[PDB]
Image (cartoon, rainbow over all chains, first blue to last red; front, side, top):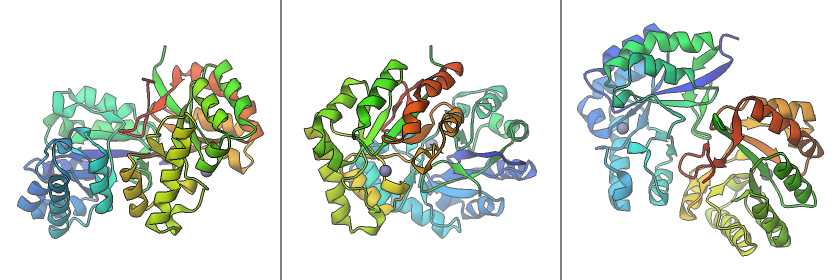
Length: 192
Length: 192
Ligand SMILES: [Zn+2]
Ligand SMILES: [Zn+2]
């Protein structure tokens, strides 16, 4: 098949002055992805939140200000998550069903807050390290490790991530894998 | 010796078939997570311990295996709490992992999981061993697993027991080892 399996491409920390270029690259290369936006940036850039939707992306919750959430009390975690639901929905991004904790850091209290808002926690299977100066080569290599169902962490801002997009599409196509959405039931990548 | 880890799991024990399964796993150098029902843990405390003494991890699979999403919250709470108590009381530790019966979940269930400090664990591959899968098919399902991925098997099927040596060979051939399931990510990782 054209798609023998699906992977979860994801981009944290937008939207941003880098977002439109990234979205254009993804669509031109036939890729869809989940954008884990910060609420403060969704609030500041509602038109870019919509641009993600119009590009064929799914929009998800990445907290309001990107704190270390497990260092917060429950009320503060609740504020961070709820304000982000509101900012994304208000901007036309839908009401997210997925949440990625900043730094991947979680605890039972955070889990309770996620459940309150009907959010599935989404970590990752592979960290592209694009936030930690990974080369374009290294990012493409990280994508090459993904199997059916697996999710990769990338970010909205790195230049090497934007440069990687065509080779990411090539890597997936070579393997008979396609870009998929992330199931709120299982947290793994599935057919859109 | 391990290029990566997979999550072997067995639902619905313990049972008159458990000790045979444990012996096969240990003889073939495998470890796994046993998702026990609370009622069977209560009925067979010595077999709960046998799982620990064989090198397995023990997790929560509800008390009576209801369709949890058809229950009220207090009923879900009783099913999960009594299973925590039954497993810990039998010497299986206090579980960190919970698999919903039938893989069926909702936000209410997620809230209850969080209250008890439980990470929800579905699966990446269903072996279909509960649905009359042949030994060949079960081995084939294991062959689809990549690093981090989790497979659903059950404690009782004869073909699952028969499959253990070839499961071990399949994994060893790929440099994959049997791992623990992370409470933070729900992915298979190196045993602690
Ligand atoms: Zn982030
Ligand atoms: Zn079951």
